[PDB]
Image: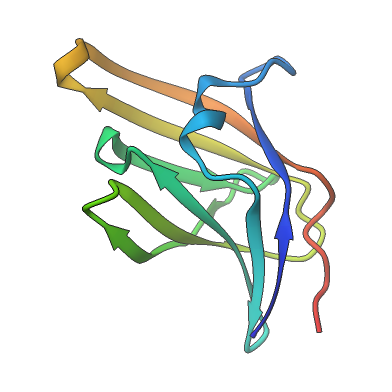
Length: 121
């Protein structure tokens, strides 16, 4: 596999304002290529809060996600999101539930990469 870091920012639906969700993913992320498949690998923090997450490309196709590291002690989850070179953003739809703080909401957010997913190797 070949990999490199990638900067990204989660923005509110319909605005350039940073979404609160930006704080709940680790920065930077990573692009990895293995056997002709590319992934955006990202770490969800406070993983227990994330009841659902779905990622879509700019053609509104849902992208496969795979959990690769579930760190229960740290309450983080590392996932690989299937991408292709040239993707500039992902629509990221979440359902966040935190019963202890009376919180249960769905959000659509716009995850903007600093540059398009690169070709690697």
